Length: 49
Length: 41
Length: 49
Image 1 (tube, rainbow over the protein chains, first blue to last red):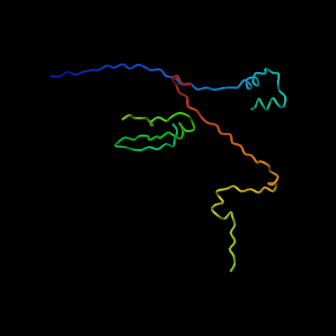
Image 2: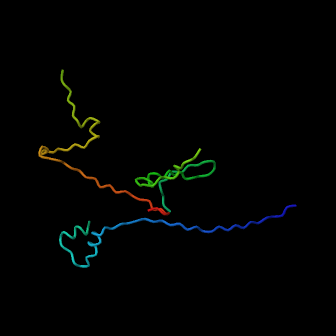
C-alpha cells in the first residue's frame, strides 16, 4: 500500500553582466573642458561637431 | 499594453510567437548569430 | 510612313535613374559625392575586448 510523497527543491541565482565601450578623443575633451576661455566663431563649430 | 507588429502562429493547441530576429539584431555588427551552431560527426 | 517619337521618361527604364540638368558640366574636373554610414553594436560579457 502506497503513501503520498512530497518533494522540495532549491535553485540559486547566477550572476552575469554586460559591457559596452564609449570613446572620446582628447581633442574633444580639450574642446569641452575649456572652462570659459573660448567662444569665438570657429571654436563654436568645433564644439558643436 | 501596446499593440506591436509581430506574427503569431498556432501549433497543436498552443499559440506561440515565431521570431527569426536577424534584421533587428545581429545585422550590421560583428557578432556571429546563434542557432548557426556546429556539429561533429 | 510617319516615324513614331519616343520620349525617354515614358519608358520604364526611367525609374532606374535620377536625371538632372547641368549646363556647366564641361568645367567639372572631378565631381565628388560622400557617404557617412554608422553601425550599431552588441554588448556582451566574458573576457573579450
